[PDB]
Structures are given as structure tokens and as C-alpha cells.
Image (tube, coloured by chain):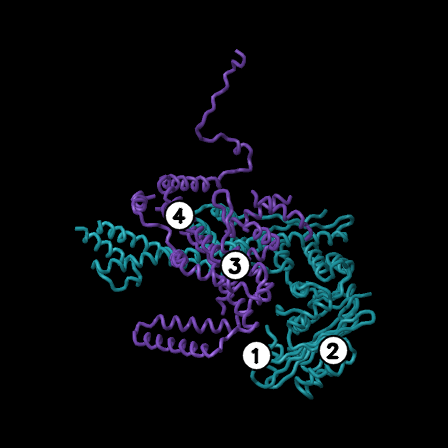
Chain colours: A purple, B cyan
Amino acid sequence: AQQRSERYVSARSQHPAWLLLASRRAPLVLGCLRTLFEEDALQALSEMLAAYASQATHLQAGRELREWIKRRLVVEREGRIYATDALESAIQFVDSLDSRIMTSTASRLSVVQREIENLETGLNPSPTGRIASLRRRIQDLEHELARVEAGHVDVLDEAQAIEGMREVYNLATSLRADFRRVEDSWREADRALRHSIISEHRGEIVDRLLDGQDALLNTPEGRVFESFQQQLRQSAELEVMRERLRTILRHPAVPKALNRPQQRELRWLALRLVRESQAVLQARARSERDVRGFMKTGLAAEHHRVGQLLNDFFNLALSVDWQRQSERRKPACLPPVGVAITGVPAIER
Amino acid sequence: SETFILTSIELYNWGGFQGYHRAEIDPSGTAVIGPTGSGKTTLVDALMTLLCANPRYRDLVSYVRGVIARQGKTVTAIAATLERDGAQVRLGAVLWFEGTSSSASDLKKLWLLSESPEQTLEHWLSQHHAGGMRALRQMEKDGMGIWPYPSKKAFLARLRDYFEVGENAFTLLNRAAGLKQLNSIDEIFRELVLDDRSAFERAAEVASSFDDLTDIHRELETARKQQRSLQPVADGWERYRADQKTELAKRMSDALKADTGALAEVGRELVDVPRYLERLRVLTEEALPEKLKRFLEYLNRSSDDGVTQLLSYIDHEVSMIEERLDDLNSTMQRVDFQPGRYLRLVAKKVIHESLRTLQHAQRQLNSARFIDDEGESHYKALQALVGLLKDACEHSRNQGAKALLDPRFRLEFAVSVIEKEIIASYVLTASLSYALCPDGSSRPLFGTIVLDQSSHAVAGRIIAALREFGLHAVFITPNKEMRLLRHHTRSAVVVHRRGVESSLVSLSW
């Protein structure tokens, strides 16, 4: 019980999402960032911060943007800004305060029961139990078919139909939750690999890594994403799912269950899923290519020794008197590099 | 006008006094004269028991049992009355012992604050004698101007709210009520005016947190050492897949040397080679990132919420001391120590070797945060500062160590005349006047103070200063200075001791 409070305090101090939520300008920052991912970031942030004085804009806009970049809420790669998982967690929390779909329903209970049955029968190696389960399910389906042949077709009521539609939307919309998480997982592996290469720099490690064709940057989330995207490619079931969704969306009870944006999201589910899954493998390939290029450049030892020398110089610099203009202007010991020759004074000759 | 002044003190079986006793106070001045050890300090201890949480006497049990003159079931009560133009307030206490179990947790106490004229000491005693505790807490439902508290904390909070004073006025009044000798100016100002707000407690917590962080650092180092040993086995397996079995066995032996239980029972067989590899993967993808993340989080939190805030707190305390000194200097202007002259206080920061070392270490800590070493340099820089704090806190009875964690010792005070006894008395009186006055006002609501002690001219200015600041005084003297008090004080309280009993007689000159 005591450790929970310490964990909460640590999360409050460190985690980017809670810091963003507790920030002074949280609502406008959240709105602007969410609009963006749907210089230019700095310009739009300044524009939004302009007509919200209430409660020198361009200076504080840049200061806050660099503060969030430091906190790793957003990431800067070369000259571009990319979103992380903390931003999406904050957005999900904020925009769920208005409308949240209930999960204490009968449909969710039936789904849970069927899923538990499926898992339990899938973990069983004995063949006799499998045969018994198959026979029981076949008999139940045959009984239902016999009942239906007598003219007892069952149709969900309006309330049950609305409940089912909302539950299906809630389950289907959760497949995009962890797309940024995989990329965040790969970036830290990249950083750790580069740090290990620099601190080691031994050329044998670099040569061995370059020689092998086995891919680097392996993480637990990457394997889960690979397993997901492999099954995503089996179009023989994606087509059936899309057709069933199209059939479902043409029902009288749809307007009372979902509004326009939700209907749009359910309408283009498969296309958007495939399109967004294809945009993560490219990021992984780019990361691996950049790592291999950095390794092939071969300037790690220079970085290490220049860092050591800079640390020595900075340690020494604390023992001099910077308050005297005489010492601040004393000539140092550094050679001329990139000498630009004096213009010949012929001028007009 | 609008200032309460003390009028009387009543005792009942308190210390060496047996039964009921009463002492009067004059509106101008009063001297508590009597032979040494006859009970002069007992009266003031009884008065100060009602005003501060921890008086500097040796405890309530000794006074209750008359350390023994009273054993077993017993009752003791004390009271004090303050009056003004058309108003009266009374502060009292009743403490009793049920039996012979003389212990700290067996003494039952109640504190009383009253305004109605029907609440007297004898009424409280009668109610206790008739109903014990319930009859004492019952009078709140049968009257209006009575407030009982079975708690000194709430009682003192209410008392400090009644007279619109700060949280340290009564502590200062108690400190200057038994001071023996007027010492040097720095010693007086550093011991009898400023409050003790040293930061020796936070240093221990910071040191404990750092010692906790060292364990996480050690775990991270162990994990890195294990991974560095395990990698050559992975290299050797690739070499073998391309004799070399001896080198592979040697590498597996080296890997097993550094293991701590993961590779518990394995061998140098080629069948066990995959197992080693799996362990390496678990090191690379799961354990090391988690340990590094936890280490970085703990390092940042300890470096920011730990040692950084302590020094800022100390600097803020020094700034508050300087501001209060400026306010005291402003207060002291409205008086003439000499014709057309007044005193002024100046504060100058001192320097010490420990302070210079601490500041240099702090600069190193600030400079080490810009290195990208995965926190190694930052940890090394923080370690030296924590070590300095530990060394300072270990020996808390030295000038160097107290110069670090005690704000009052980071300054030196001087007095300007823009005589030691007169200057000390003026500073003490100005501090008392500043403490006992509501903000934005110059008239105290609590007026009575107690003093201990010099020719006639020496004491002739103290009385003038007290009258100028608007304070009523009660002096304590032995039977030695009964010549000048006759000219200033206009009443006297005499304590006669006969055996193990004392009696008080109040008379005018």
C-alpha cells in the first residue's frame, strides 16, 4: 500500500502524459497537436496561442515545444516532428470524458464466455476431449437447424441490435491502439545499440554486426506486431469481413446506435488497417538502414575520445576566474583552420 | 486602552505550594522578591506552562507530586487572569492523578479558556470533585463563555487565534523569561531571537534515498557484466557453424563464472549451447531496458526532489532572516537610544572552507547534467555532494558543519549607533514588541512580559523603552536590588519558605 503512493509520485514526476495533462496550457496544446496529426508546428502553435490570451508569444511557443521534445512527449528525427504513445494515451483519456461505451452488458458477457471456451478447448492436447467437444457442438448446431426448419427464425430486438452494434464498434476500434508503441520500442533499441557501440569502440563488434544479415532491433512488441500483420494479409477473410460490415451498416437501427464519424470509421476499417500496418514496416526498414549507415561510417572512437577530452576541459574550466575581463580575453591555444586569404589590395589594377 | 494585562495568578497544590494560593499584579509594575530556591521559579513555570507547548523548566509530574509530598490520588489546578477596559479572559488548567501509578501516561489533564465571570478555580475544583471528568466537560452545555480542551495543541491554536499573534511569539516570550547573562550580540541574536530551523533531519532522508539508489545501480552493473561475458559464446557458436570446441567450452565456463543463478545447472555440451543463447536474448531485450529505465527514473527523482530542494530551502530561510532583520530595523527607528540617535542591525554573510567545497560540488553537479553517458557522470557527481552532506550531518557540533545546515550560522550580525547590557535589552525588547503585535498594527493585545536580571542609570533606560513600546513588565530579583525597584515597581510579591511549604504575600511599598 505504501509503495503504490511512491509509484504514483514517480509517475507524476516522470511520465510525459501526466505532465502534459497537469501543464498550464494543456487544453490548447492538446487541441493543436491533435489537429496537426490528422516550424509549421511552431507557427500553428503560435497562431492558436495568439487568440487565447485571457487567463512574446513566439518565444514561449518555442520554449514549450522544446520542453515537450525534451520530455519525449513528441520526437524530432531530422527536421520533422512525430507523435508518441503518451500523446495518444492522453488524447484517449481526454476525449473519453464525453461519451464512453458501456462494457457491463450482456453481449460482452457472451463474448467473454465464448472466448474462454475457445481458449480452454485450444489448450487441450488430448484427442478424446477434442472429439467429444466437436460432437457436442455439431449436435447443438443440428438441433438449432432442426428448430429453424420449423419456422422459428430468431431476430434481435431493437435494443439488442443497438447493444450489439455498439459493442462491435468498441471491439473493432481497438485494433489501432498500439501502432505507435512498436515504433517507440524500436527507437529505444536503436539508441541502446548506438550507445553500446560507442562505449565498447571495438572494431570487431562492428565488423561482426555488419557481416551478418540477421536483422537487428528486435523487441517483444515487434514479434507481436509481426504475428498480427501476417494474419492481416490473408485477404480471403478480409473480404468476407468487409462485406459483412457493409451488410451490417445498412440497417434501420444504425442511426440510433452510431453517429456519422463512427459509421465512417466502421465503413473503411479494413483499408485503413492495411494502410496503417504497411506504414510501420517502412519505418523499421528506415531505422535499420540508418543504423547500418552509422556503423559503416566508422567515427565512434573519435566521438568517444572527443567526449572524454571535452569532459576534461569542462572539469578544468571550473577553476578559473571568469569575473575578470583580463582572463576572459587572454589568447588561447587553437590553430587557424579554414584560412581565408586576404583580398589582394590591387583593387583597381 | 485595547491591551490585555495580567492581573493575578492562582495556584492549588502546585509544586511546593500546599492548598490555595493567590498573587496579585499591579498595572504599573511588580517584583517577585524572595530568597533563592523558595519558589520564585515555580510561579513563572506555572505561568509558562499555559503559553508554550514545551516549556524550558523538570516535568509536570514533578510539580503535581511536589518532588514526595503528595502520593496517590491527587488534584492540581492553576489559573491566570488578563483584563482590559471592559473585558476579562482567564486561562486555566486542571490535572489529576487517580492513584499511586505515578507515570507520564497516567496523568489526566484539561485546559480551560473562559470569559464569563462565573468561572473560577474553586468552581472547577468543585466540578471535578463532584463528577471527575464528565462534570468538567459538561459545563460547556450549561454556559456560554467557557471552552474546555482535552488537548494542548488545539488549546494553543485557539490561544494564538484569540490574541492575533504569530506561531513563535510565546516561545520567544518564554526564552527571554529566565535568560541568565547578556552574552555577545551574535550569541544573543543567534540563540534568543531567531528560531531553530536547521535542516539536519532532511539530510538523513536524502542520504537514505541515495543509499537505496546505489542498489539499483549495482543491479544494473551486474546485468551489464553478465551480458558482456555471454556475448563471446554467441560469437563462438557462429564460428563453430562455419577444433574450436575447446574455446567454446572455455567461453561457456567464463559465462558460468559470472552467472548468479540463471544458468544454474548446465554443461559444456553442444546441446546446452542454445540455452545460453536464450539467456543472452533475455538480457538484451527484457532485463536491461527495465533496469536502465528504473535507474534513470530514480536518479532523476533523487537529484531533483532530493539534494536540490534542500539548498534552496536554506537560501530561502536566509532571505527570510534578512527580511525580518529589515523589519526589526524599521521598528527600532521609533526610539532614541541616545538623544537624536538610534540603533541599526546589519547582516553580513560569512565564508568557510566547507561552504566553498559545497558550492564547488554543486557547480560540478550542475555541469555534469549535460553529458550523454546514460547517467553515469551525473551519478558520480551526485555521490560526492551526498558524501559531503553525510560528513556534515555525522558531526553536528562543529562550526563548519553547522555553517552548512543551519541558516542562523550563515550570517554575522553587527550593531550601529546611527553599553552591552543596554544594547542587548533594547534588541530583546524590540524583538518582543515586534513579535507581540498584529500585522499592520502597533498596539499589542498581549502586554505582560517577564524579565530577569546594573546601576540606577543602567536600568533607567530599560523602563523607558518598555513604556515606549507599550509593554507591562514583571521582574524577578533576589533580595539584592531592593533599592531601585522601589522607584519603578509599585508593588511586590514575597515568597516565604518554611520547611517544605511556601506562601505568597502581595503588598505595596
Q: Percent position (x, y) of residue A63?
A: 58, 46
Secondary structure, mark 4, is helix
Q: Are marks 3 and 2 on the same chain?
A: no
> Do marks 1 and 2 both belong to one polypeptide chain?
yes
In the picture, measured across the screen, residue A289 lies left or right of residue B146, that is: left
Is residue B482 visible from the viewing direction of this image? no
Give the CA separation, mark 2 to mark 4. Answer: 83 Å
Q: Position of residue A268 (x, y in %)?
A: 51, 57
Name which residue type carries label 4: Ala
- Determine which residue is flagged by label 3: A267
Above or below, B66 relative to A240 = below
Side (left or right) of A12 relative to B96: left
* Chain of the residue on which disc 4 is drawn: A
The residue lying toward the viewer, choosing from A281 and A340, is A281
Local crowd size for mark 3, using a 10 Å CA cut-off: few (<14), some (14–19), many (≥20)? some
For the residues bearing labels 4 and 1, Cβ distance under 8 angstroms:
no
Looking at the image, the residue that sits furthest to the top is: A349
As drawn, B281 above or below A112? above
| Amino acid type indicated by mark 3 | Arg
Q: Which residue is mark 4?
A: A285
Could you confirm whether marks 1 and 3 are on the same chain? no
Tag 2 residue = B146
The chain holding disc 2 is B
Q: CA distance from mark 4 to mark 1?
A: 75 Å
